[PDB]
Image (spheres, coloured by chain):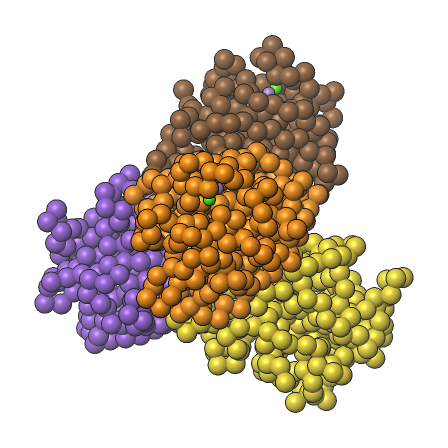
Chain colours: A yellow, B orange, C brown, D purple
């Protein structure tokens, strides 16, 4: 199976697989069952911002998710990613819907990684229809509204259920290197999760994977396009 | 054929393809025959730095190549690259040798492109043996001395003739987009030693169509960039 | 007198100091009479973006001013700023009003200078009421709407006439150094509304000696930059 | 008194004021008695590198000090700097000598702070004789060898004792802002501590202070130019 490190913006409590009984943000290290979560007020139809930060010195993977009204949720997890991630990775965004659905629209995404310097930095503040530096997987699509639709949206604009999709940056990322004194990464994305369902589901994740990571089969819904099972 | 924009550090004067009669830096737009050149003193065995600068505003592709002693050569060419390059490109380093040879060692390479924002920036100040975010073409190799040898160097450290190689950054780059108010790029690389009577053939920073490959027969004076000298 | 290099967004044509007979962007080198101008459609009440670009390599000071609808004006001037500016400078925004007026509201300002490295980069996408890393001169104020009002605006939001103000970045900037292979700077700011029959007088990004102050009598057409129109 | 947050590269054990009984790196929050230290092998005459990292999300001030042979020491301290530092600060480097001495030469210094964006980033890879964007205090001098000599060095090159000096970046830095979701800073400097003394002393610190911070009187030696006393 792939190796996954992720920050999940989990809109739907799957309390049967360890989700807290509210929407939450989580840090996922090789499991959809987050090593740490925080209660998250997802604001339907509002543009949220997620920032993810890690460095090899503090060894603390952190994320904050905020909306324009000031509300935010933060979660941090002490982890030495040198010991979890392959040296080379791809980085991406994933999202899913299941029985319940939502738009999992990404409006921007930036990422920086540095080994201290080697560095990779990309920023998408607009996505093209033919976003050649993105590898789209599953239902993920770009263009023509400048956004990245991680999961299926019909032409009328309504999200679809049982959808999973991801967008990986095209280039592999050298995420750690033994000679490096510091290896840091940061990611920011903005998103717009909207649903008229009974409940929104399932969420968006920023993830770091093996370079050849693919959507595991059956990873819609609770599995967020990141894992083959809920273990 | 590929579409190439390149800044060449041309160590070897090939005067019947229109090179000046001295080593030179050149701006190449879709031709190995540089639109503009400047005399360049390649300092054998010294680490050089090339800086290449463009923006969609001043529409001036500029390059400076310098050495630590301060000597430098600069060339600039007014060109609207929106009218030469595909929107999407790959960026790379190329080098070649021919009858005469030189090491074509890249010690570092950075690149930034911004559309104003979408942006891509990378920097390699050390290359790895398996540099997964580089597409190596031809004779180019990395590692583990931290360098990118664009052209073949044997075990004894002697550069080989009729070698060509390139290194492209893995990801396509969105180098211009018509609504961009500013589409700027910059590249810097550090790098050439030869015990030949003359070093050749040079190194280029280049920007190419995404699927660019070394043109057949582009060793020597063609710098791995062009299928011919037209 | 101060030494000024400026990019002016000149909303008001003062044709007997050599302005063109339309609103324009201009590159000013030690004179309010721009060395180069381009016709500029200031879009009343819309947020504009100015980008200013220079490097010691192409030696071309360029500016583009644009609006969200895509309209834009660009001006470029070939100049070796090593020969005009002191090595150390302050960088700023200036604006003025005269008989006619406009808000001269800065919504953001970034600046990068690099000597290739020594570097300074700042960005303000929000200004604070007490913006300690800005030196405000004349009528310029910040806060707490997140903006920098270079010129006086009364409570009712009406801009006042014969207002001049500037905002300099607190730290001196080492804008060139003779050994620098590349001394580049860039600045971007976003910003103008008037119910006057004509907006005036404009906004400038400028680079000045470190101790630069508003010249006496530099409201109106002098843009807070120059003691006279010579 | 000033408010000081600092990362100290403490070359001299003052075990009578809480120093561990070896050279160490430390995180100093309003006291010279470090809240956390790590044993540090200062390599006489070698060029070391210090990286300091903090962000308002993880709230962990971290530092690593490394030398070209690979040896490094790291120290991290969980602290919410919002609650310690004034909103506006100056950032600097300080060093001292006492009864024992060393060069406290800085060869480069970079700093970045961001509020998420407002940002300040400066880099000095060479210091000029007239480094106008540095406020030099005490014995600190620049030019003409491209370095910043935090403490006194005689013309023959030997460091002097009972020396204290600092270099602050000229502009105040907006280090936190209540509206910011993230406020991060990073600092890197390289240094060359060399001594032919019986023991080197006293060390170098990167520090963040109130904007009007000055060398406290009598802050040579153990106090590293940062504090008025050893409390
Ligand atoms: Ca869930
Ligand atoms: Ca040639
Ligand atoms: Ca005018
Ligand atoms: Ca001590
Ligand atoms: Mn979950
Ligand atoms: Mn040539
Ligand atoms: Mn004018
Ligand atoms: Mn100590």
Give the side of residue B112 with respect to residue A39, left or right.
left
Q: Is residue A204 above or below residue C188?
A: below
x and y, in percent, of residue B35 in the image: 55, 36
Along the viewing direction, whichever of B57 and D29 lies nearer the viewer: B57
Q: Quadrant of residue A44?
A: bottom right
Q: Is residue C198 above or below residue A162?
A: above
x and y, in percent, of residue C47 in the image: 68, 38
Q: Residue at x 50, y 75 (%)?
A: A87
Looking at the image, the residue that sits furthest to the right is A156
x and y, in percent, of residue D141 in the image: 23, 46
x and y, in percent, of residue D58 in the image: 50, 69
Along the viewing direction, whichever of C204 and C198 lies nearer the viewer: C204
* On-image quarter of the N terminus of chain C: top left
Q: Is residue C132 above or below residue C94?
A: below
Tell me if residue A51 can be seen. no
Along the viewing direction, whichever of B149 and A86 lies nearer the viewer: B149
Q: Quadrant of residue B30?
A: top right
Give the side of residue D7 with respect to residue A77, left or right.
left
Along the viewing direction, whichever of A132 and A90 lies nearer the viewer: A132
Q: Residue at x 65, y 46 (%)?
A: B85
């Amino acid at each position: 199976a792939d190796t996954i490190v992720a920050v999940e913006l989990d809109t739907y409590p799957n309390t049967d697989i360890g989700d807290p009984s509210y929407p939450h943000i989580g840090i996922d290290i090789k499991s959809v069952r987050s090593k740490k979560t925080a209660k998250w007020n997802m604001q339907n139809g509002k543009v949220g911002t997620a920032h993810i930060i890690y460095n090899s010195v503090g060894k603390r993977l952190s994320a904050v998710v905020s909306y324009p009204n000031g509300d935010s949720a933060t979660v941090s997890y002490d982890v030495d990613l040198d010991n979890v991630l392959p040296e080379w990775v791809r980085v991406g965004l994933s999202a899913s819907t299941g029985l319940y659905k939502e738009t999992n629209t990404i409006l921007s995404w930036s990422f920086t990684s540095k080994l201290k310097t080697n560095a990779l930095h990309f920023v998408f503040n607009q996505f093209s229809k033919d976003q050649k530096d993105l590898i789209l997987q599953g239902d993920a699509t770009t263009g023509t509204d400048g956004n990245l639709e991680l999961t299926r949206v019909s032409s009328n604009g309504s999200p679809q259920g049982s959808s999973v999709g991801r967008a990986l940056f095209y280039a592999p990322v050298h995420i750690w290197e033994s000679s490096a004194v510091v290896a840091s990464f940061d990611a920011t994305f903005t998103f717009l999760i909207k649903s008229s369902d009974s409940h929104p589901a399932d969420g968006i994740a920023f993830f770091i994977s093996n370079i050849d990571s693919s959507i595991p089969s059956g990873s819609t819904g609770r599995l967020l396009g990141l894992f083959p099972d809920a273990n």
